[PDB]
Length: 145
Ligand SMILES: CC(=O)N[C@@H]1[C@@H](O)[C@@H](O)[C@@H](CO)O[C@@H]1O
Ligand SMILES: CC(=O)N[C@@H]1[C@@H](O)[C@@H](O)[C@@H](CO)O[C@@H]1O
Ligand SMILES: CC(=O)N[C@@H]1[C@@H](O)[C@@H](O)[C@@H](CO)O[C@@H]1O
Image 1 (spheres, rainbow, N blue to C red):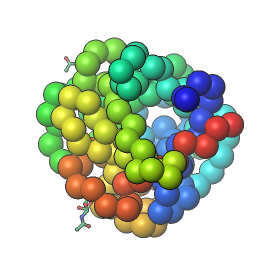
Image 2 (tube, protein in one colour):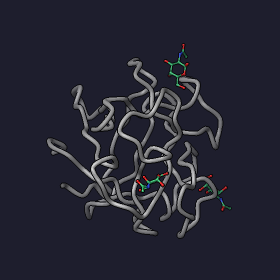
Image 3 (cartoon, protein in one colour):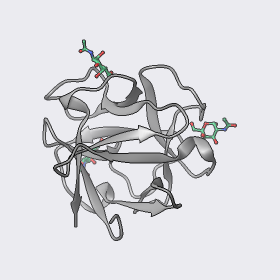
Image 4 (cartoon, rainbow, N blue to C red):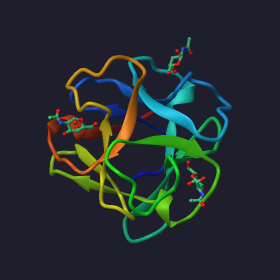
């Protein structure tokens, strides 16, 4: 129930969400990407604000998941980045399909987190984006540490 530290795992590929470059201290607007590796710089915390909306926090840096530019309605294929700012456009909802695999939905726009290109096997360092489509390659699993 979303307390503690988690790996965010892409169902189709098994890859994880990382800051690009994997650093403990990425600057603002660093891209989020998928990558196979596991380490403490790919852990996240979920901060429950109530009523099923969450801030997604990078453990190592304390920065949050944003759409690049922070719009209420980002276009399809808008990059997800880390940023220290907080506001309504960096909130997310987790929708369970019913077996513990989730769509990760941007509250403001209703778009979902996808690997860019939607592959079942994104290459390492593929950017994560927002997109309106739903399919099995935009499901994620939250793996507690
Ligand atoms: C050696 C090392 O930490 N490598 C990291 C890797 O684990 C992953 O975090 C990646 C994400 O872009 O960034 C680097 O290549
Ligand atoms: C929209 C705005 O006024 N500021 C935001 C900032 O808060 C953050 O969301 C960032 C993410 O790239 O995009 C803009 O710079
Ligand atoms: C046709 C096809 O592959 N569509 C996908 C789409 O569903 C979405 O996953 C997107 C994310 O960048 O990548 C592709 O455009």
